[PDB]
Image: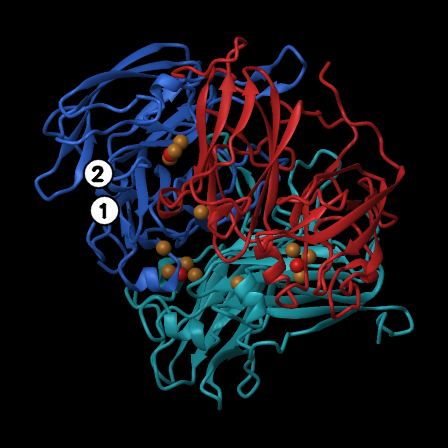
Chain colours: A blue, B red, C cyan
Amino acid sequence: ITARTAPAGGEVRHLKMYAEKLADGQMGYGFEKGKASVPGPLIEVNEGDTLHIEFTNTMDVRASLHVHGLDYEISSDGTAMNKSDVEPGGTRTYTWRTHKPGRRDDGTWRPGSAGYWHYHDHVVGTEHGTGGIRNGLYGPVIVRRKGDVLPDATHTIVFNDMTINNRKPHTGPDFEATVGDRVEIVMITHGEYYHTFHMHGHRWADNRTGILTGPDDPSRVIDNKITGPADSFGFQIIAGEGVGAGAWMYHCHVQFHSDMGMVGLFLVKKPDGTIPGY
Amino acid sequence: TARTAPAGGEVRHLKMYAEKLADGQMGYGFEKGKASVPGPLIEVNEGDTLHIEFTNTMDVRASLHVHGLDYEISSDGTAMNKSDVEPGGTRTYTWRTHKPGRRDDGTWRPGSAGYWHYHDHVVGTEHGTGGIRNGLYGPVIVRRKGDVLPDATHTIVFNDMTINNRKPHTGPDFEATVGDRVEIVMITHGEYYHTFHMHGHRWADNRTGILTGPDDPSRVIDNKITGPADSFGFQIIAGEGVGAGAWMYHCHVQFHSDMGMVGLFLVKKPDGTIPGY
Amino acid sequence: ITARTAPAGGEVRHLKMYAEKLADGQMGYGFEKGKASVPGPLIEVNEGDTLHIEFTNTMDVRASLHVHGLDYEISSDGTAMNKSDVEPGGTRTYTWRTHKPGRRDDGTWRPGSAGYWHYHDHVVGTEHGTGGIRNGLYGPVIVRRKGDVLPDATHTIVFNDMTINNRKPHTGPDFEATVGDRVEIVMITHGEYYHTFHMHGHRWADNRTGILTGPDDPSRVIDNKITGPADSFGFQIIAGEGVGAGAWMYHCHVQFHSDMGMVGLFLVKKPDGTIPGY
Ligand SMILES: [Cu+2]
Ligand SMILES: [Cu+2]
Ligand SMILES: [Cu+2]
Ligand SMILES: [Cu+2]
Ligand SMILES: [Cu+2]
Ligand SMILES: [Cu+2]
Ligand SMILES: [Cu+2]
Ligand SMILES: [Cu+2]
Ligand SMILES: [Cu+2]
Ligand SMILES: [Cu+2]
Ligand SMILES: [Cu+2]
Ligand SMILES: [Cu+2]
Ligand SMILES: [O-]
Ligand SMILES: [O-]
Ligand SMILES: [O-]
């Protein structure tokens, strides 16, 4: 493999994070005050890393940080029940850990932390974060295994109820690549509805990485994936591989959802920057 | 050095009843007056045969239908095939299981092993809609030789918008000690899709919920979409890498968790305490 | 393996197809005028094959052909946006390609096209084909890998909203086999609803082929599979294996759906043609 690959983990990392009310009534996470986003910023670590997150709640209601997949003690689970949320104006340090896979004392195989995961609020509106998730308090987390192939770019697509990334219907988001780029997609679902994520012109493996290890990998190859609230998966594709440049739609394939605006464009450009037809 | 399942091939006999419960629910049991919702766990090894003498103590027809396991049409539990049971009647159902292996044509026949379930097929409608709603469902585990055995098995059924037909916000809660090998059988019934989530723990999305080793490509998840009659299971080490605590499990459909589809996996320290209580 | 198996692909194939309004208001695809069907005809190719489809729209509204899984250039994506649909009475040639898996220049493993796929309209009623799909413009596509086991027969089961193959409730379809037949099912979902496909007396592997490669195959074995709009999977079973002859139900296991008529029969006959009980 002459693609770039992830190194062995084991670093201690520190991060500052905020929750902020946005002017339009949404709520977002950010690494810097005044720079919150929906979805929140991507967090990327290597198996074995530890992450300490000093989280400041700048809002006038309690809020928290809850993460899927990664190791955390009960004091970092982000729930009111376990006294793990954060009062208005307060600050709390959360700790997320990750571990490599390996053989247990009893001979069984402990799975590693690697995967496409996500974080979100757990106390805004209800004790399950229903109002916080609705308002935009969610973001992606990637844990890489040593040797995983690294992409040119990562895009995050969140089906939150009947919106993509809390955007107005029929406003994408769109993103751009050049034929041949290695593009990574993190796909997260939140809210009340099931969805089916579909991409024109591209396909991926329904496994941890979205990639086949080789000719022995039995994972199915798909272009359409059912998802429900708090499901997270990811994959990498070679933009335009075997199909060329174009305005490649991605959308939820539930027909009513598609018709109501759950559609975006994967704009794959020729080496001269053009898109066939535009 | 964990305990593992032996090779199967025994003929087993079981008595089972369907009973109307005082509150209007219906449940299966191994003994009259000891019916439960979910019904009792049935556990066999690949190659075993199970003969179930089933007695319907209710005033309506009822049946037993099973997923995954081999049965002849006379044991499919449907009215169509005359395998339901009249009120007060008794019928012997036979379920079989087989090991995987090579067919004459060189193809690979899959075994019966898996996390399965049984349920009524004739109460209320000819698809068991009323019987399932009333509580006539239960788990079945078929083990492959060499499968790792747990310390304890718990059954979690999302039946419409309830867990195990319980009132909203009443669990069920389960208890373990840090380090216990805990097995979960997860079954869905009714009209709704759900997403099963556990705080602090994760499992492999494959037959056993466990990876065979470094080559196992199965994804590792903590959130699984499920629909009516889906069944899966897994094993976790309670509190592994995360410690003791009151660990929530719930459906992650936001309205469903808000409406009460939540329980607690109470993982105790060796002194019996739960951090915070 | 002394079963029949798929050969290596790499042929250029040509096909004529039509879209046709049916007397009852449905719309169907066909290989010949007056022989349209819902589902449309099965298209079956080998990895490496190319397929040129000369598609004629005989209807009074625009219509198109969009395919999942297979390689196509943007000019064959079947969307209005990319000028890829067909005006009333018009004709257009679509090209679908397939490729085998293999090693990329960077050492990564490119997945092949093989799988259980499907095609459908993309412009009737809305720009996502909502009206065309509703009316019956969908059909199965199988791409075989060299060495794949070939069945005795293939049946296509489409959960389209709350119908099977657009049929009236409680009218099947029913299929017939003899104990020991190798039967292939292509299972496609369309519309607005999620479903769970269940077959009495039989089970399959939740992987690309529905079959285990051997004792090392980790895929789960199931008899109940959740599906959403534009999901497609398939499998092979040995009719009556270990269970014998009988009227074996298949249905959606959503209780309201089976009660409302999403039920059919897999009629597995003894060598004398009878079905136990009839
Ligand atoms: Cu939670
Ligand atoms: Cu959707
Ligand atoms: Cu498409
Ligand atoms: Cu969550
Ligand atoms: Cu049934
Ligand atoms: Cu739910
Ligand atoms: Cu969680
Ligand atoms: Cu069932
Ligand atoms: Cu589309
Ligand atoms: Cu259905
Ligand atoms: Cu069944
Ligand atoms: Cu489609
Ligand atoms: O959660
Ligand atoms: O069933
Ligand atoms: O589509």
> B200 or A257: which is nearer to us?
B200
Q: Nearer the viewer, residue A57 or C157?
A: A57
The image shows residue A276, relative to residue C174, as above or below, that is above
Which residue in the structure is indicated by mark 1?
A: A166
Vertical comparison of B268 with B232: above or below: above
Residue to which mark 2 is pinned: A38
Residue B71 image point, x, y percent: 81, 54
Quadrant assignment for ligand 9:
bottom left
x 69%, y 37%: residue = C217
Report the residue that reaches farthest toward the left: A23
Q: Name the kind of residue labelled 2 in the image.
A: Val
Asked if the beta carbon under badge 2 is closer than 8 A to the nearest atom of ligand 4, the reply is no
Mark 1 in CB contact with mark 2 (< 8 angstroms):
yes
Residue A256 shows in the view: yes
Residue A93: percent from left, percent from top: 26, 15
Check mark 1 vs ligand 2: CB closer than 8 Å? yes or no.
no
- Answer with left or right where residue B96 lies relative to residue B119: right
Query: Are dots 1 and 2 on a single chain?
Result: yes
Point out the tag, 1 or 2, that comes first from the N-terminus. 2
- Mark carried by residue B116: none
Query: Which amino acid does the dot numbered 1 rest on?
Result: Asn
